[PDB]
Image (cartoon, coloured by chain):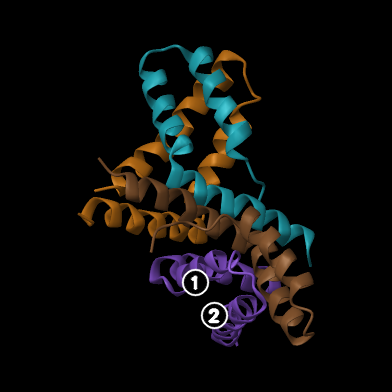
Chain colours: A cyan, B brown, C orange, D purple
Amino acid sequence: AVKILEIEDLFSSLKHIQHTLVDSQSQEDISLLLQLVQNKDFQNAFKIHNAITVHMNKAS
Amino acid sequence: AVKILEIEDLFSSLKHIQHTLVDSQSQEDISLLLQLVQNKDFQNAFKIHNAITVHMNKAS
Amino acid sequence: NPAAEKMQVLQVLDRLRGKLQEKGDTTQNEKLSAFYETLKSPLFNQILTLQQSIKQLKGQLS
Amino acid sequence: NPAAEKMQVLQVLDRLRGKLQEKGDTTQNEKLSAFYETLKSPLFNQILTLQQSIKQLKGQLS
């Protein structure tokens, strides 16, 4: 009841999606996510949730 | 107050201080920092302040 | 406002993923759903809000 | 109590560093001065605050 994503896999995902959609407008939207995903501060927030979530399901 | 800290360096530091501070009570206090420093969630937050700090001092 | 970006992002996640499922890529879709849900997460939003404050610090500090 | 640990931590940083300076280890001091100070920072604090909330979840939820 959570499911993570890991910006690392999510980052490579957008890269695929970008070269997978190549609909121009799609690359722009994709790039948007890519920007946030690559954002230092943003990445920090997501990184916290990722690891902490893992501990949530892991450590009872 | 913006010279970062680096947990890797700060972690190895407590390790030294731990063996260097053989007053027993000091080991307990040292371990305290060690625990926080090694804490998954804590480590994440600290990392946020580390990089964001760097970009802070940098500025335009 | 910043919320405009995140809002567009969520809609962007659903849009992009839609094209994938339409193109035949139901692999990255899980990422768009995972990224979309997490983005919507309450506590998660709080984490971003915090970082947002830090952003103001760098923009206000001079 | 949360503040109890952090309060003891800052006090621990000053104590530890004190022994080092007394023993002849004025090297780790920079870590204790930065760790301690950064700990005091309202920004770094708010970050841990949110993280603490999440910990409450994993600790309360069953």
**Rendered view: C34 above or below B41:** above
Q: Report the Cα–Cα distance between label 1 and label 2.
A: 7 Å
Decide if residue D37 is in sight here.
yes
Decide if residue D62 is in sight here.
no
Give the x, y percent position of residue C53: 33, 59
- The crowding category of the residue bearing disc 1, from other C-alpha atoms within 10 Å (few below 14, some 14 to 19, many at least 20), is some
The mark found on residue A37 in the picture is: none
In the depicted view, which residue is nearer to us: A15 or C37? A15
Query: Which chain's residue wears label 2?
Result: D
**Rendered view: C28 above or below B14:** above
Asked if marks 1 and 2 fall on the same chain, the answer is yes
* Mark sitting earlier along the chain (1/2): 2
Residue located beneath label 1 in the image: D39
Side of C47 relative to B55 (left or right): right
Q: Residue at x 71, y 70 (%)?
A: B17
Q: Residue at x 51, y 49 (%)?
A: A44
Q: Amino acid at mark 2?
A: Leu
Residue located beneath label 2 in the image: D10
